[PDB]
Structures are given as C-alpha cells and as structure tokens.
Amino acid sequence: ATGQDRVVALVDMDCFFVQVEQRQNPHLRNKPCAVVQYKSWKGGGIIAVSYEARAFGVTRSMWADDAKKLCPDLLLAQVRESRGKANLTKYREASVEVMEIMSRFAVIERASIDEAYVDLTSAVQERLQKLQGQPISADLLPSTYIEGLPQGPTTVQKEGMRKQGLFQWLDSLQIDNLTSPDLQLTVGAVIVEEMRAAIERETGFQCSAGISHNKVLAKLACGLNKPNRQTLVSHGSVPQLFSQMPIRKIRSLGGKLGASVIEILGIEYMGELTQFTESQLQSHFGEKNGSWLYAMCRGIEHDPVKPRQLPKTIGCSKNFPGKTALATREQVQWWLLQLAQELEERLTKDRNDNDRVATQLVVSIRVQGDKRLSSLRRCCALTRYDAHKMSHDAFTVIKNCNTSGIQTEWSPPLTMLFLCATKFSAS
DNA sequence: ATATGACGCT
DNA sequence: AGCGTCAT
Ligand SMILES: Nc1ncnc2c1ncn2[C@H]1C[C@H](O)[C@@H](COP(=O)(O)NP(=O)(O)OP(=O)(O)O)O1
Ligand SMILES: [Mg+2]
C-alpha cells in the first residue's frame, strides 16, 4: 500500500479574469484591481480580484461599492455583460487557449474556467528513462516549493528560504531507483515548470501549480505557494501539513458534510481522522465515505484524472432577485428567448469546434418564496439549434407551473431562469 | 440582492 | 429523470 502510485498535478491561473482584462488594459498591470459583474446594485458583485487588491483586503461576492470602501486604488475592470446577463466570452475563449498548452504534455481534466487536473504518470516514466541517472538540478525548478523543508537542526528572505529548501530535497533523492515516489513526484515537478513556463510563454498568463500523488493533495499544494510558483507535496509532508489542516478545506468537505464530519466525530483537522478505522468510519457516513475519508487523512485518494477538456452541459442562467422577479407571461417568454439566444450563440461555437450536438435541454426556475438554487428541473429533447424553438420549447415545459387563473400575469413571480443543453453527441 | 458546471443519489 | 451538494 502506498497511494503514491500516480503522479498528478493541479495547475490554476493566478486571478484569471484579472489577467485576461490586464492583457488588454495595460493600466491594470502592477495595480490593485477587481472585476465587477453588472453595475447597479452596490456597484456590482466582484467575482475576480487581483493580488494587489487582496493586500488591501478585497474579496469576491463582496459588492464593488463596498470594496471601494476598503480599496481606493481599485481600478475596476467591468465584465462585459450582454443580453442582460453575463457574457464570459473573453474568458471561456482564453481558458480554451490555456488548456491546449497543458495537453501538449499530458492528457488533463478540465476542472474550472481557470484550473485543470493533469495525470503526469505516463510522462514521468518518459523522462525518468530519458535520464540515465543524471541527477535533477535546482535550475530546472526555478520556482518550486518543497512542503516541509528546510528542517531539523537549523536568512529571512522568502526566496532564500526556497533555495535551501529545494536544496535539501534533491540531496536526499534516489536518482537511480526510478521507482521511488519522491523521484517520480520530482521528475513530474519538472514537466510542470516546463508546462507552466510555456503557458506564460504563449499567453502571457501566469499560473501556479501543486504536485502530489492524488488530486485532493495536488490542489492543497497548488494554493500553498501563490502566486507564480508550484509546490510539490510529498506523501511524507502529508502528516505534517494535514495536522493543522482544517477539514473544511478539503474538496468535498467544504459543506454540510464537512460539519457532520467535524461535528459527529468531534474534530477540527484532517489528521485526527487517522484514529478511526475504515469500517468503524463507514458506520457514521456511509460505505463510500468511510472508504474515502479513511485513506484521505492518509493522503490516499483514487479519484482518477478524467480525460476531458470540452465539458458537458452548455448552460446559461439569469437571476431576477426581489423586486425584479418575473411575474408576467410576456416577461418569461422574452427572458426565455434572450436566454435561448445566448445558448444559440454558445452551442454553435461548440459544434464547429468540438464535433458534438446536444440532444437534451433542461429548463429550471425558482419561485419568489424558495431558498433552493433550483425549485424545478424540467426537460425536453433539443432537436434544432433554434432560439425561437428552444424559447417556445421551454415555455410549454414550464407553463404548467403558473398557479393562476390570471393568464395575463404569472403566479407566483419567478426569481430564476436557467437553460442548459446536455447529452452531447458525436457530430 | 453575489453566474456557471460537476457529480452522487433516487 | 430530477433533486440535493459542492466547487469556482
Ligand atoms: N464565487 C465565484 N462566483 C463566480 N465566479 C467565480 C467565483 N469564484 C471565482 N470565480 C471566477 C473568477 C475567477 O477569475 C475564476 C477563477 O478564480 P478562482 O479559482 O476562484 N481563484 P483565481 O484564479 O481568480 O485567483 P487564485 O487562484 O490566486 O485564488 O473563476
Ligand atoms: Mg479556482
């Protein structure tokens, strides 16, 4: 048993949307900025935030007019909004630049607009053989941080720290035994400096990464050292790091389950999960959660890097909160249309680029009096890439919710509308 | 009154 | 198929 079988990495762009705005507005470069969505209610919900604006304390979800309370220098690059909602075309088109690069190395799995898991297992056996045993040098890793080094019997500069830390790791390394989990992790951490350096080469976009043995730890190390650096995380640094690591951090456990993992066990850290055996664990969460949250605090997860760049489900959403809420037949046709037209714009730019037709179409709504993000999923075969079809397709599918005799309006007002095309074909 | 996309379960 | 959960 090891869980050091694979080598897996998680690259991720340092404040992506800011970087995409900055490559057209040079005034934004080396300046503390955010990126705002719409512009009326509190100036617009801030989604992306530069790192110079973070050092004044500006957060996402925060409302533009409220960071302009925290941040005077907050040169605010507005998101392009179109058809009344969002238009994220600047970025979804950049994101597809960045993932072309990363696949020149290993077959990755798209994980966000801005990040991608990548399995480097095969290509590590590529480089390791290309080595006759020629030890790996520091120069090859100009920006890699080694979790848990330096140490033992022991400058102040953050970047001298990084040298004498990289320098310890390499010296204790079995450059011959091509099977050591810390020699494969280490070749792999090169493919990623070369991956990430060629990104900023071909895009001007800056990335950070994280490189352990599974995917939950690749992420946990991506965001250790940021921005513009990587971090290898050894299966031996795992017990160290995991010990002060909050359960709420780990991918899956950020939510309701997290609390129960914490509450039901009486815990606050990943490392304290070690003491409960697996079938022991399974009795409080399930047959799959115990099998998982056991080997997790042992830095063993076996979620595979699922080979996928072009996603599934093309989707287009628009909220109508509070006083906006649509209560009118005529409204819920125009918004359905304007939603059905951006889908039309996205779905074509799919079909030529990616060789697939979606056959499904999922309408959703929310009502002025529900908390659930969605209060009704309803579905109907997408046959033709027509807005006016999809628009009128989608009214038939939902009309049967208007609790009214007033067919002049809508009872009760809708606070959300969502069109999503799933079940792509081979076109 | 913060727009997307995935997945496990039923 | 639809809904809850979770991540960004
Ligand atoms: N709650 C949210 N809602 C909508 N969009 C969001 C979002 N959070 C992030 N984004 C959008 C905006 C973001 O530009 C994009 C990816 O942002 P991140 O992966 O969350 N973190 P970033 O790459 O920005 O910087 P760093 O990694 O150093 O934290 O997704
Ligand atoms: Mg991210």
Image (cartoon, coloured by chain):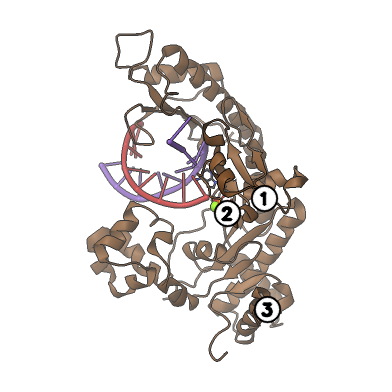
Chain colours: A brown, B purple, C red
Element type at marker 2?
strand
Disc sitting over residue A166 in the figure: none
Q: Residues within 10 Å of mark 2 (few under 14, many from 20)?
A: many
> Which residue sits at x=56%, y=42%?
A46
Disc sitting over residue A98 in the figure: 1
Marks 2 and 1 sit apart, C-alpha to C-alpha, by 10 Å
Instruction: Depth check: give the residue in front, A177 or A271.
Output: A271
Determine if the C-beta at disc 2 is less than 8 A from ligand 2. no
Toward which corner of the image does residue A158 lie, by quadrant?
bottom right
Mark 2 or 3, closer to the camera: 3
Relative side of A306 to A370, left or right? right
Callout 2 and callout 1 share a chain: yes
Place of residue A292 in the rendered image (x, y in percent of width and height, measured from the top left): 36, 63
Callout 1 and callout 3 share a chain: yes
Circles 2 and 1: CB distance less than 8 Å? yes
Quarter occupied by the N terminus of chain A: bottom left
**Looking at numbered disc 3 in the image, what kind of residue is underneath it?**
Gly
**Looking at numbered disc 2 in the image, what kind of residue is underneath it?**
Ala
Mark 1 or 3, closer to the camera: 3
Give the vertical position of A79 relative to A301 (above or below): above
Circles 1 and 3: CB distance less than 8 Å? no
Quarter occupied by the C terminus of chain A: top right
Q: Residues within 10 Å of mark 3 (few under 14, many from 20)?
A: few
The residue that disc 2 covers is A116
Marks 1 and 3 sit apart, C-alpha to C-alpha, by 31 Å
Place of residue A127 in the rendered image (x, y in percent of width and height, measured from the top left): 67, 71
Relative side of A59 to A132, left or right? left
**Looking at numbered disc 1 in the image, what kind of residue is underneath it?**
Val
Chain under callout 1 = A
Toward which corner of the image does residue A326 lie, by quadrant?
top left
Instruction: Depth check: give the residue in front, A298 or A415.
Output: A415
